Image (spheres, coloured by chain):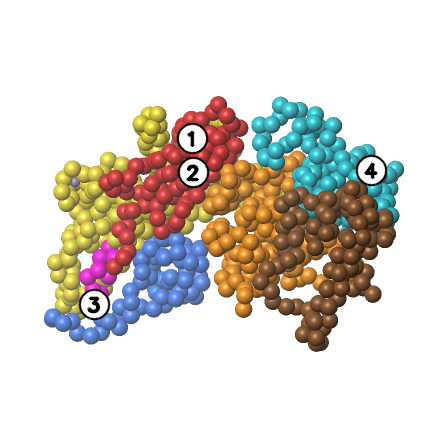
């Protein structure tokens, strides 16, 4: 397994403020079901994306998904573990903080995930029940695939 | 893990220019072939200059420098000629050098143009590209110039006098589809000669999976080596350098293992 | 009000202590009155230091030059030992004092 | 001083193109047309003839050290 | 003035600014070529930020290898507006300004004279203080 | 007065070896190739030919200092495949590529002249 988050997202906005980077846009996405607010920086020229497209967003601690760590090294000869290749767009990054609305006594009911994919950042807000899998300073894989 | 098969077509081929396109090949090999055009191609140029009398208003090493830059026809005998460093004989011999003799004295009042025509070689194969006339120095009445020069075999790495080629125009991806360079305003950039797109559009759509291929060449010879011999000797020299590296590597591997 | 809210360590809440401190240390902090006395003494000393600072630094200039960067090494300790802010700590406040 | 052969930027021979350039300038052509007729398409070559000044003529005015 | 006097200056600084942006993405061969000029590189190629469809590294990802040890520093890019710290996107930085270096890895931001330059609290100052002169020398040289 | 002789980018004087192989201890089965009196013309050539090999994990070239004439090539392959063998195979690959290119260019020139 090794899966941290699984949901289907819809793109509501692209450039609420503007086009700061030509090759990188910021997907402002609202999710069905879980009601997961997502902000994501996606490289555009390699993986184009426009408004209002259903894409499956998958957050996984490992790509093999059989329960083994990836040791954080790039080896193209690692096909034999049957890496999860069902997704068109794959990112690797590191979550750098977890923010929530908890204050002293009461617990956090809603959390926000801050993951940096080597500079491309993402915010993931929603109820903490399904977002509890994220731990600060842990390697995270982002998986994307367009849907009809 | 093996060679891609390169293909070549020759668009324009003259006595001073050859224009060819290399396809289905890597960027680095195209660049190295371009660099060997300038650097590694052997050629015959004057190196050893001895002046007996120099009455010209230009001092000795000035006219020596001008002589060294004079191109010499080496289309054939540059291969059989050996480098003076590797030659068995001391100084210079006909198997390692070519002797040039210059002897001009201005007797008439009008200025005499000492040109490449006045250079006299011992062998008829190396003519200073005179089948106008390259000007060495001008002489007024009473001035004289006599010198003896030897021409050696060298390549562009040593000195620019051994450059066999004029400006080598190299170009790949004319309509910018790989986005190797990003135009801040693509509309104001003139379309290349090899551009394949229509006039209205500026750049081809970006190709994420593309890699540099179809490297357009334009080799302009300086008149010493005819332009196709330049590229042929360039390929031969690059292959020879690779083979020597292979031999030394094999010897090193056997020695260390 | 902010100084007291930030530096007092109000132990009476019994819910903030559970949230931030380990379950074992909460009973130790509450039961023993010596813990509370030492903590109140620490806060009193901190208030005296506040008064001394306000005497030393009029105009409220809080930027000062000091040998070692406390916040930076606190952050370094958080990262070296993989400290998780989401979880209660195992550090006894009397041990800190 | 004198026209430099082997244009510095690329290396094309321009030491033989000075007298012809002077003739073309003197008879009909402007500098641009004269340079075009000499086959100098790269501006690095055209700057060699166009910006050249020929002090070799001035140096020939003085009597030689030996007659 | 308890500041570093040497700093990444002029050409290398401008190229650092242009290289640290989100916009930059480096292919396999360019990554290898850049990596060999890193004297303190351990020999392990980091996994690219983008894996599919093609492996693309990022300027910050490679720069994080230059940063010695585990350096923690927070700076702000010269472009950083004052509205960001007040409202939302405080830790998201839509213009990718501000600087966060966590566990010796450049997580986000644009580097400029405010980070690698000769100023108090600069990234190089933190490198000298936390690590030492010898390692900071290699940090300078590798950056250059 | 300190200008080096023009023949120091290609000429090997007494003592230096044309190539040198030093194993890299930081990572397994990775070697360091040091080529003396040589520059980007082949540095880039073996750098790019190595990347064609699927069994090469790391490949490149660099010049330690432009005023000196030396190339350091670092090759890392998959286990059970020596980097020296990969470097040799790449050189032979480039030799074959150049020979084929020369033959095709001669054919093309024969087609262009009186054809
Ligand atoms: Zn001889
Ligand atoms: Zn020119």
Instruction: Specify the chain shown as blue.
Output: D
In the image, the segment drawn in magenta is B58-67
Vertical placement of residue E10 versus B95, above or below: below
Q: Relative to the observer, which residue lies in front, B121 or A18? A: A18
Name the element at disc 1.
helix
Q: Are marks 1 and 4 on the same chain?
A: no
- Judged by its main secondary structure, the magenta piece is helix
Q: Colour of chain B?
A: yellow
Q: CA distance from mark 2 to mark 3?
A: 52 Å
Q: Which residue is drawn at the image coordinates 42% and 65% (left, top)?
A: D31
Q: Relative to the observer, which residue lies in front, B41 or B224? A: B41
Q: Colour of chain C?
A: brown
Q: Colour of chain A?
A: cyan
- Number of other residues with Cα within 10 Å of mark 3, as a class: few under 14, some 14 to 19, many 20 or more: many
Q: Which residue is mark 2?
A: F73
Proximity of marks 1 and 2: CB atoms separated by less than 8 Å = yes
Q: Which circle marks residue F87 in the picture? A: 1
Q: CA distance from mark 4 to mark 3?
A: 92 Å
Return the chain for callout 4.
Answer: A
Q: Which residue is mark 3?
A: B57
Q: Colour of chain F?
A: red
Ligand 1 image-quadrant field: top left
Residue F11 lies left or right of residue B216; in this view the side is left
């Amino acid at each position: 397994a090794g899966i941290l988050f699984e949901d289907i997202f819809d793109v509501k906005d692209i450039d609420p403020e503007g086009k700061k980077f030509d090759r990188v846009s910021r997907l402002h996405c609202e999710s069905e079901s879980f009601k997961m607010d997502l902000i994501l920086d996606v490289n555009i020229q390699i993986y184009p994306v426009d408004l209002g497209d259903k894409f499956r967003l998958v957050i996984a601690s490992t790509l093999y998904e059989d329960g083994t760590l990836d040791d954080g090294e790039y080896n193209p000869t690692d096909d034999r573990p049957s890496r999860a290749d069902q997704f068109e767009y794959v990112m690797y990054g590191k979550v750098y903080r977890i923010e929530g609305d908890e204050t002293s006594t009461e617990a956090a009911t809603r959390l926000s995930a801050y993951v940096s994919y080597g500079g491309l950042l993402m915010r993931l807000q929603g109820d903490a029940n399904n977002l509890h899998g994220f731990e600060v300073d842990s390697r995270v894989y982002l998986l994307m695939k367009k849907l009809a | 893990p093996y060679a891609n098969q390169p293909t070549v077509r020759i668009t324009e081929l003259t006595d001073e220019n050859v224009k060819f396109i290399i396809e289905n090949t890597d960027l680095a090999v195209a660049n190295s072939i371009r660099r060997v055009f300038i650097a590694e191609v052997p050629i015959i140029a004057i190196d050893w200059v001895q002046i007996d009398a120099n009455s010209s208003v230009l001092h000795d090493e000035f006219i020596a420098h001008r002589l060294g830059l004079i191109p010499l026809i080496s289309d054939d005998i540059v291969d059989k000629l050996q480098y003076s460093r590797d030659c068995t004989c001391e100084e210079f011999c006909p198997e390692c050098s070519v002797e040039f003799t210059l002897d001009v004295r201005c007797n008439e009042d009008q200025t005499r143009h000492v040109t490449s025509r006045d250079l006299i070689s011992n062998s008829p194969r190396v003519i200073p590209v005179t089948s106008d006339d390259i000007l060495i120095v001008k002489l007024r009445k009473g001035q004289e110039l006599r010198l003896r020069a030897y021409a050696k075999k060298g390549f562009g790495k040593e000195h620019a006098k051994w450059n066999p080629t004029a400006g080598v125009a190299f170009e790949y991806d004319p309509d910018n589809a790989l986005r190797h360079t990003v135009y801040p305003k693509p509309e104001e950039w003139p379309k290349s000669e090899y551009s394949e797109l229509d006039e209205d559009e500026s750049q081809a759509p970006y190709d994420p999976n593309g890699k540099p291929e179809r490297f357009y060449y334009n080799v302009e010879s300086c008149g010493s080596l005819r332009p196709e011999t330049i590229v042929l000797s360039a390929l031969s020299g690059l292959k020879k350098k690779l083979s020597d590296l292979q031999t030394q590597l094999s010897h090193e591997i056997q020695s260390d293992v | 009000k902010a100084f007291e809210k930030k530096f007092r360590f109000d132990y009476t809440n019994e819910r903030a202590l559970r949230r931030t401190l380990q379950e074992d240390l909460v009973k130790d902090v509450l039961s023993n009155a010596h813990i509370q006395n030492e903590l109140e003494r620490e806060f009193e000393r901190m208030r005296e230091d506040r008064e001394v600072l306000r005497v030393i630094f009029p105009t409220g200039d809080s930027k000062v030059v000091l040998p070692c960067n406390l916040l930076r090494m606190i952050w370094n300790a958080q990262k070296i030992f993989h400290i998780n802010p989401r979880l209660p700590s195992d550090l006894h406040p009397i041990k800190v004092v | 001083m004198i026209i430099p052969v082997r244009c510095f930027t690329c290396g094309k021979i321009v030491g033989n193109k000075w007298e012809a350039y002077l003739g073309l300038l003197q008879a009909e052509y402007t500098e641009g047309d004269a340079l075009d007729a000499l086959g100098l398409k790269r501006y690095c070559c055209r700057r060699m003839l166009l910006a050249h000044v020929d002090l070799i003529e001035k140096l020939l005015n003085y009597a030689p050290l030996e007659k | 003035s308890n500041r570093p006097v040497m700093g990444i200056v002029q050409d290398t600084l401008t190229a650092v600014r242009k290289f640290t942006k989100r916009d930059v993405f480096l292919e396999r061969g360019e990554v290898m070529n850049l990596l060999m000029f890193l004297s303190t590189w351990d020999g392990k190629v980091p996994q690219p930020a983008i894996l599919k469809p093609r492996p693309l590294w990022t300027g910050k990802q490679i720069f994080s290898l230059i940063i010695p040890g585990h350096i923690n520093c927070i700076r702000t890019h010269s472009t950083h507006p004052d509205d960001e710290d007040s409202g939302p996107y405080k830790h998201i930085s839509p213009g990718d300004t501000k600087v966060v270096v966590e566990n010796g890895e450049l997580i986000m931001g644009i580097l400029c004279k405010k980070s690698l330059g000769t100023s108090a609290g600069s990234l190089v100052h933190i490198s000298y203080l936390e690590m030492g002169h010898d390692i900071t020398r290699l940090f300078y040289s590798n950056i250059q | 007065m300190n200008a080096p002789p023009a023949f120091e980018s290609f000429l090997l004087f007494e003592g230096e070896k044309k190539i040198t192989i030093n194993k890299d201890t930081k990572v397994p089965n990775a070697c360091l190739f040091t080529i003396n009196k040589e520059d980007h013309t082949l540095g880039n050539i073996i750098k790019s030919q190595l990347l064609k090999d699927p069994q090469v994990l790391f490949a490149g070239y660099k010049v330690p200092h432009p005023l000196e004439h030396k190339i350091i090539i670092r090759v890392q392959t998959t286990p059970d495949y020596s980097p020296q063998e990969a470097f040799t195979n790449a050189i032979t690959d480039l030799i074959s590529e150049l020979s084929l290119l020369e033959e095709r260019f001669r054919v093309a020139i024969k087609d262009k002249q009186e054809g």
